[PDB]
Image (tube, rainbow over all chains, first blue to last red; front, side, top):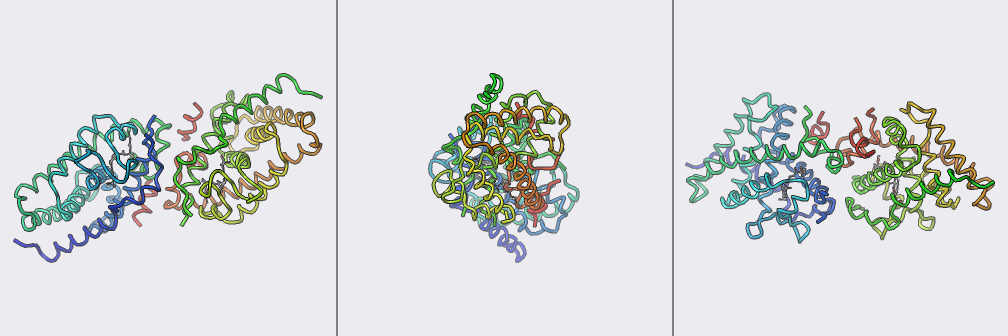
Length: 239
Length: 239
Length: 10
Length: 10
Ligand SMILES: C=C1/C(=C\C=C2/CCC[C@]3(C)[C@@H]([C@H](C)/C=C/[C@@H](O)C4(/C=C\C(=O)OCC)CC4)CC[C@@H]23)C[C@@H](O)C[C@@H]1O
Ligand SMILES: C=C1/C(=C\C=C2/CCC[C@]3(C)[C@@H]([C@H](C)/C=C/[C@@H](O)C4(/C=C\C(=O)OCC)CC4)CC[C@@H]23)C[C@@H](O)C[C@@H]1O
């Protein structure tokens, strides 16, 4: 039943990588452009995501097996899954009491109306908050939450991957660690693995709807100029 | 001796354009990334210049004759003279008492050491502060200061200009307005016009030294990512 | 090229 | 292309 020494070392490396790339106090948020309550919240949220992308890359470089991939596969995996990984780690700040992301006082409390002040319609915000509620109800352990992000990041079905045979080999080896951990250390999780895999397909729909609204913004220069060079590079179509 | 009706209307349009694109209170400075005392002041200064570029473009669009030029000449004139026009309008905040730009409290007071925290050596900062002192000693009127920026912007000797015959026609017509205004409304300015033209050649050396240090930064992505999409476009080499 | 400058020039 | 991503990947 129990895990092996090499499977637990994968857990020791992912949890440590997440602690090194996530701040539960959100102290670096003051270095962003201030939030403003056309598209007033766009500068603050653009810095918030650009800051998150830097942390996702730091977390990716510490995933066992990710660094041995080619530099092109690392880019294709990061570009197509960046917004999905960000939506996963954003649940750590989401709260079911106010139905919003809480990162500080009234300034860093991102309600549903605040994201509307960035150009996003309710066609994406309605399933996104629905995703945060369903994910928050799972009460995932810290090991399970960091495993879901590594599995979502190592997906072979990403546009631009080349050696997708090794990518599937790394993802399935990451899936076996999660599937076994729930059987051993998570009581009442006889159906948890299927619910987490279901959340991956939900992120694909959130990724698709996000890319349509971002594409509409990227063509208008008076709005895309408020973005950061990293966001334009990750969410861009260059290859 | 006196001016004509069409020459004074050029003055009424430039002074109004400068008032519409400059804030003596510097209230929009809080919307930038906060200043931090490797390259800690780079995010704040990158937003400060990107904000200034937007105001220089607004001031350029209200210069009489600039809007009738081709869209390509307007870009070639703005790109090659942006840092020069910015250094001109920056004198409005410079103070000889502390030898620094004063835009607010201790946060928006940009000393010489603060610009060093952006990657700039003293090879550019030493002549730049020397330029601000010599320009501040001239005690230029508001009409003379706005005329110097329009003359600096309409320079024909810019890399990338095409119809430089009309550009020289507009600059010399702008020079005659300045040369006559000093003779009429500025007592003790028998030598002022030559001193202002001398400051234009000084800006060319400041422009050259600025482009060398920016070029060294632009090749390092970990630093150029802290810039804005507008700064990368104006200070870039694309054509 | 210069997509923002074209737009900023109205 | 992707000059920042290459650098951010060390
Ligand atoms: C990212 C994290 C956090 C919150 C994330 C949130 C809450 C607010 C809404 C966020 C930012 C979501 C929004 C809707 C997504 C935005 C991006 O596309 C972006 C904005 C706009 C844009 O592209 O407009 C195009 C029309 C370009 C920057 C993502 C995660 C969501 C907070 C902490 O838990 C840290 C974590 O790391
Ligand atoms: C621009 C204005 C003002 C101040 C301007 C200043 C004072 C501080 C120093 C400033 C910003 C000067 C500095 C040295 C120039 C910087 C740019 O190149 C920049 C920085 C760094 C960079 O490129 O590093 C490459 C190695 C990319 C953003 C310009 C005007 C100077 C303040 C007000 O009067 C409004 C006016 O509108």
